[PDB]
Amino acid sequence: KTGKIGIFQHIIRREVTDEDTRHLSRKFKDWAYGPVYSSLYDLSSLDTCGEEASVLEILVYNSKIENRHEMLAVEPINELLRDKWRKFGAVSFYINVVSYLCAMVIFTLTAYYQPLEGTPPYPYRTTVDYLRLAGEVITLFTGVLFFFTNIKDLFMKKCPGVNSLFIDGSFQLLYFIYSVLVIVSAALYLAGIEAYLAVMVFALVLGWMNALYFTRGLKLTGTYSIMIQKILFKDLFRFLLVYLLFMIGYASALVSLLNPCARDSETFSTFLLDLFKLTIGMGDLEMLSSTKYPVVFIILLVTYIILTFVLLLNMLIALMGETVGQVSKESKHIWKLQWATTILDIERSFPVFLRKAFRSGEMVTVGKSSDGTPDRRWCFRVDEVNWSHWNQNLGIINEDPGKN
Amino acid sequence: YLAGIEAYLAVMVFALVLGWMNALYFTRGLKLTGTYSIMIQKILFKDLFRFLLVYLLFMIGYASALVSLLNPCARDSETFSTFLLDLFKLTIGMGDLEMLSSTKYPVVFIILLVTYIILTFVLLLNMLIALMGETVGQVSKESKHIWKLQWATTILDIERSFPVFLRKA
Amino acid sequence: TGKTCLPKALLNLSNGRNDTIPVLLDIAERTGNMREFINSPFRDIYYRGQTALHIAIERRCKHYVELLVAQGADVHAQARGRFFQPKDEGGYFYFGELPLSLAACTNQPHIVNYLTENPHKKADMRRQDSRGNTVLHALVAIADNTRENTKFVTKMYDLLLLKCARLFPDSNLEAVLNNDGLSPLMMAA
Ligand SMILES: CCCCCCCC/C=C/CCCCCCCC(=O)O[C@@H](COC(=O)CCCCCCCCCCCCCCC)COP(=O)([O-])OCC[N+](C)(C)C
Ligand SMILES: Cc1c(C(=O)Nc2cccc(C(F)(F)F)c2)cc(-c2ccccc2)n1CCCN1CCOCC1
């Protein structure tokens, strides 16, 4: 929880040699046959399905994000997450992506097939229109359930801090907004306020854009979508500042050099847009309109084209230094923090009896305890090959070198 | 063509675009054309279905949303393919903005479309950026290995086609 | 798993003695089976050919390899198990299934210089296992490209290549083919 690698890596890999105290150890040694030995890590607090707090749920959810990507790789945690991915993890994730995309397809057809008319357009009454009602039913079933799944997980776990915004903090806020808008929409639908379809169409533009969650799990397109929130926040709200230090400048300057109707004048809402047309190509320069100083008006205009090409190239190289490859290593790190979140969120939603059916490792008689009873752990096997230290004959548990 | 079917100009012209794209095999004779023609594949097989994944969520997104800001024929409707022309018309600086078409809530149609402008450039920037770090930070040293494997395969394919006594010459 | 008294002794070592072993050979001299007692393989489907000669070379225990060779165990006993299969075929450690091959694979030269050069039964280096791999094919099998592995493999590959040329001058060992057709060079490519 506190982010301390140095003693976390030592406790999780503690191998106490002497015979008197071997029940304190956590990295055992199962068998050996020449240069192949079976290190046998002890899962005792690392993977406890349900009936305990867990070190893996603490590292993924309630840890410190500066060291979180370094602690989820120590000895067993990296293989423990892949063994919880080769199992239930990967398979039950792609069930959700084919279900949520279909949940947005059905939501889309309810927007396109809608007879927008005044009051509630209710009286379905035919073989065509009951598909529109039943689609709206499924729409609200996405509505109330995304509300509950977000909030009941929010206050209880996952620690809604300001630093987890790329570790499913932003999507923690967007799936709330998707459930807000769909509640307001179906309310205004059944009431009678005509603006229901405007409220409905903000759930179209959000939800398909909120389907960008589900690229998490590939690392091909997953780290790509990390750049989507990276560029748009750290570099677009610091370019649109500097770009609007010229658009509140030049545009409020050039229209000052313009006859006040005494095109003529008093269409500044278009005159703001008319300047923007010139910077991308689709301009006319009819805004000249025989003004008072056309020599002055054109050397400010050709200045503004350069400076908005200067800033546009500056945005590009700001996406080279503050952004890319210094960030391309950090997107790899923050992918695994989103990846390990994906396995655990599935594994937290299973019921306990099924969650115990998908355990990792195996129950191993690991040594004679102090009282003389067998020590029955839940160890996890990691095989390893060593060619240099030719003395792999140690406190071996099973003298028969093999997985029977 | 050997049958009576006159649709032998559709399939033929799919062949004619291939057989000139398939002459990029023969860029494998030089190192400085061979390592360039491999990056055209890695930008395609890796970094082009990546973009067309996300860009076909927004075009299956906002575009299917903006057709709901349209009268249901009461152009009028039934022509959603034409609006897919109209959407892409606007973003690449050749639109007209006449595709408003009386728009039951008009100001909604601006703020969603200007979102589609500013968001898809970020993705278009991201094609210039996320590709820059992932590919050429490594592929400038990596694709010269893949070329050497393509160059050695070519030499062993020319030899193997020869007869034995010619190979013994 | 048809272990006998003698493989059980050779699994459980402590400073490499287990002092039962020379005594248990002496009782085996009085009853008399020794070409069946020392040559009793495990009839398991997981260790199917492993004998007491394999375990004594395994546990790095030369002086108890000398006793089992002097009594003549089964030098060239093939350990055709399922554990002794390659990493692709289910098994963990593939060493070419032979006691000279097991001595050359686990960086153990002094048993290699004793199994081939002894008063008793010799381990000739031209023998093939169940799939064709000789003592030089199996040094290519365990040849992970790390720094320490390539140090003794190349040292033991020559030491078996030279020694076959001395004893058998009419045959190069690196012509003897795997049942896939491969040579020890083509298996490395
Ligand atoms: C090629 C090599 C690999 C080969 C293939 C792999 C080999 C191994 C594969 C093994 C099988 C596949 C594993 C996944 C099973 C799919 C169902 C599932 O995940 O949960 C289901 C039930 O989840 C619930 O929450 C409903 C609970 C209802 C009561 C309990 C019913 C029994 C469990 C169910 C029936 C028994 C199921 C198991 C039957 C064996 C559906 O819910 P969810 O998906 O959790 O929904 C997401 C929830 N979330 C949004 C909060 C995140
Ligand atoms: C939106 C959605 C679904 C989903 O829609 N599943 C579904 C499945 C079947 C039927 C249906 C049907 F049809 F009934 F709607 C729906 C599932 C998930 C999910 C959750 C955890 C891990 C992997 C996927 N996520 C994302 C939720 C993210 N949250 C947690 C914190 O970040 C913000 C909110």
Image (tube, rainbow, N blue to C red):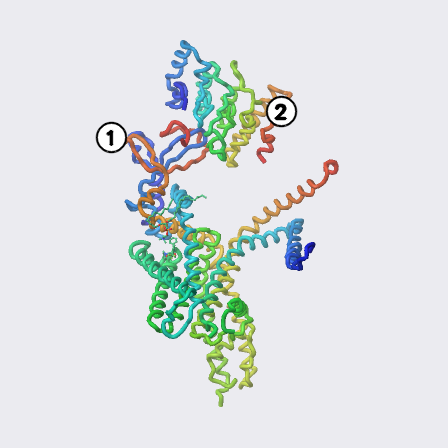
Most foreground residue, B11 or A264? B11
Q: Quadrant of ligand 2?
A: bottom left
Subunit that carries the residue with mark 1: A
* Residue A35 picture location, percent across and down: 45, 31
10 Å crowding of disc 1: few (<14), some (14-19), many (20+): few
* Residue A49 picture location, percent across and down: 32, 44
Give the residue type at disc 2: Asn
Q: Is residue A381 above or below residue A241?
A: above
10 Å crowding of disc 2: few (<14), some (14-19), many (20+): few
* Residue B155 picture location, percent across and down: 67, 43
Answer whether residue A175 is visible to the viewer in this image: no
Tell me: C146 left or right of A397: right
Answer whether residue A61 is visible to the viewer in this image: yes
Residue where numbered disc 2 is placed: C172
* Residue A387 picture location, percent across and down: 47, 32
Q: Is residue C47 above or below residue A224?
A: above
Most foreground residue, A35 or B24? B24
Q: Is residue A132 above or below residue A168?
A: below
Tell me: A300 left or right of B111: right
Residue at (55%, 31%) from the top-left corner?
A: C140
Which residue sits furthest front?
A: A126
Secondary structure beneath dot 2 equals loop
Tell me: C68 left or right of A150: right
Subunit that carries the residue with mark 2: C
Image quarter for residue A97? Answer: bottom left
Numbered tag placed on residue C16 in the rendering: none
Q: Please tell me how many numbered marks the rendered image carries.
A: 2
